[PDB]
Length: 263
Length: 263
Ligand SMILES: CCC(=O)NCCCC[C@H](N)C(=O)OP(=O)(O)OC[C@H]1O[C@@H](n2cnc3c(N)ncnc32)[C@H](O)[C@@H]1O
Ligand SMILES: CCC(=O)NCCCC[C@H](N)C(=O)OP(=O)(O)OC[C@H]1O[C@@H](n2cnc3c(N)ncnc32)[C@H](O)[C@@H]1O
Ligand SMILES: [Mg+2]
Ligand SMILES: [Mg+2]
Image (tube, rainbow over all chains, first blue to last red; front, side, top):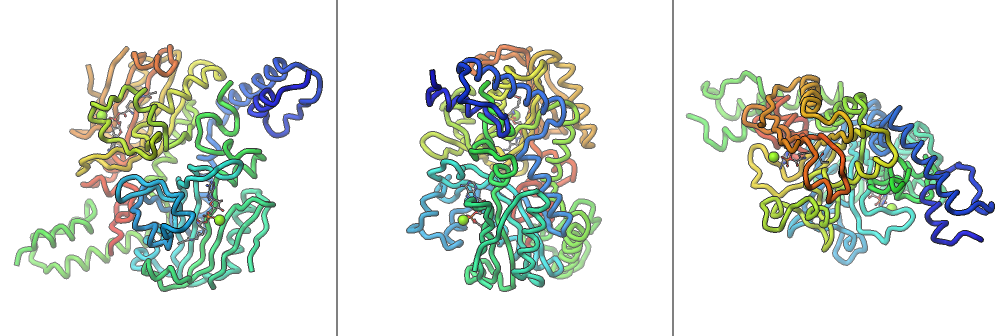
């Protein structure tokens, strides 16, 4: 008897990429399930005995080393930010991204992006640090999505930026290229001062990158050239580990390093 | 002319511990301010030229290494959790901690603690990992406080726990002792199965620790012995760097590694 769709969904939860297992084979569900449970338990046992690191934490540490070694200051700014920051980012209540904001009190929200806080750091550090000013942050961001296969409501962004000298399109592309080649992730940069560039892996957007200046800058007290880009860590993990579903790369109680925890 | 209280507040923002500067000295405000601005800019310049690491990120990486090296699995679980988890933690709407929860939708909240998610991981991993099960998480937690000098609304917790064999009071105390002596933080353990222990630095609570089992366990499908403790990273930093105000240790736009960013 062929497998049901429910049975197949269950096995797919337990399936890891390159299991090299045959589903249309003849063996009963009970046996296919038991084999996969056995392998996934062995996977968790191996992690526990050997490395013990979470993929998302580990990627964050690897990205952090990359940017610190190339002259970028590590920032840790608030996750809960004023709603006023969202309007000052030019996100009107009429816009689609405005519908995606998780509001917290009358006055606050979960940040949907790193830009507002990094803008403020750029302005502030310009009074203390020599040109060029190079900073980055990694951390949680939040957007209400009709999520599915490549959007999470709770995700993790990297944003880096440089302000002052050396803020060219060529340098932005070179940093992106060095970064992704260091992680071992395949990509192409797609796009036409004011440039928006998308870093794609096939149809999947890994990053939006910007070559400033842009008019928004003056709302944040910024009047120098700048370059920057934002990457989703879960997307990077999804590509790197060949997960079919981005939920396998998320902060989660249902997956650990892409392995089902419902065993 | 003596300094005003406002002037003194301003200088205190710029003052770092062991500046060895004399305020009741005779020199005008303008000059004292200029000296401190100069030193704080030099501090940021030194960080930028040399290490480039944020203290909170760096402490997290150091704590992570400590626990991974001693057999604990690194967890990264959701920050946004179901409100049902809070009631199942035995936090009634009549309780004070219930007033402190940041609600997000009808159904979700920002986690005020790590326990509910770690409970779920303990139950799940018990089907896969050999006894004893040893896990930890580090990350953001949220409580509405009348904050002041030692509470933040947005803070960072470490929680570790062990379940199964070896779950004794002596072992819990030994792990706490090794951890704090590794960080170089002075402490005493204060307290009388079911034990609550507070780890104190003078009057400042660094941790609450628990020797299970306790009755709550069965709401989470846990029926084995366990031990665990939760530490605030910002409190640890405050003690370690001798900050007078915990805001200097927080995720912030006003302080970087305890140095004012308003220069
Ligand atoms: C100082 C300002 C600065 O430095 N600006 C430069 C940053 C420009 C860009 C600016 N940072 C920007 O916001 O784009 P995005 O909303 O498309 O998000 C960027 C990336 O986040 C990931 N991402 C976005 N939403 C999600 C989601 N719901 N789930 C998972 N990953 C996501 C995804 O990888 C996407 O490509
Ligand atoms: C599986 C369950 C488990 O493993 N349980 C063991 C954990 C027991 C204990 C359990 N984890 C517990 O919740 O106590 P707390 O609310 O007093 O918070 C603990 C610590 O967080 C810090 N802390 C708490 N609130 C704040 C704040 N508003 N600002 C800064 N630091 C804070 C502070 O260091 C405090 O000592
Ligand atoms: Mg985009
Ligand atoms: Mg307490």
